[PDB]
Length: 176
Image (cartoon, rainbow, N blue to C red):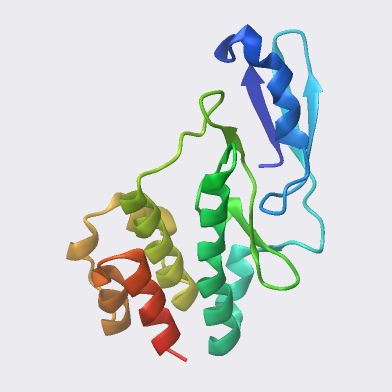
């Protein structure tokens, strides 16, 4: 969870000189360190106390939980940059202000991860909301299942049915 290996043959030779971007400070990502081996690049993540894992929010007061959940949408700012990210519990951290920070970084047209459709970003966001409100739930199971066939609480149905990202935001705002 704290190391990533990238084989060199997966990277076009003319893109080697961009791998340093994976260790450049970004306000949207965990700080990272790049090393270069014979046949691969490796990344180590700096995961320290100022970054709160997503799963820690499950025990928060409803107000603060909702604040953090609402702020997750700020990761959409990453789409204007070179970088890509994955939305998932083990990929998501928060600053001391409750702003989201991702771990793994790709680079457009250069190295995976590939970005996900808007629809799959919404499903993953929904799954995070559900997990934050019920610690028994599995993010993976929610993302992998037939979501509208989910059996759960009325709250969970409302989250699942939110038609768009903006309507999910509106639902979350309404829960205050």
